[PDB]
Length: 261
Image (cartoon, rainbow, N blue to C red; front, side):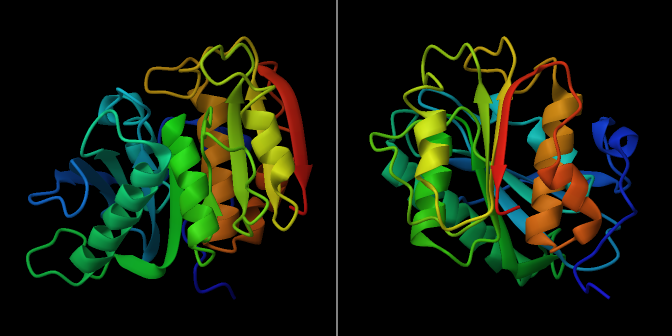
């Protein structure tokens, strides 16, 4: 029996819904350590410790762009911290450090007196996500910290697309019509560079650069896929293998590739 398995056998329906089976509370971090600001989303009733996900924004962007992931992932049994960077003009290298500082503080707060997430977190099981330079940041976090269990960046952008070092299971969410980080020059070369890992490329039909952001019209598809990947690889949850590795069954997917899943 998997000690990390939480909640039920999943269905397409249970994963496409706005919330999973866990009730969600949030708090604002009082004193952010090594990042601008943060909101932590947590399950009140997961039935065991759960892994932590740190989510980065893009250049100029703030929590509001990536906020929708917080309650979506928390409700399936993860501790999620959505962050603001020290500056909106921070580069992917700095964004990565800041995302690792956010996981560091969530982990600390698991043992911190008066913390709402006291003993809620398994600090050995952590995940990284983020939009654009925040996605680049997540990939740099993955390369520098191979004990990370899962990564799921969206519309990723970095100055280099060579992430062949990454051994962390990586879902690349891309927007087909993205003109800020075009899939041809960013999302796809990044995906292809990775030889040593379980990996997937999920491209959103008609999608502009914000196709995976808060308020997007594909939260059924994108939510299901992000939750399925994080469950399969953070929890080693083989009940999520089909949802994690299979085609989405969505008319709103323009391209789908997976290897070693």
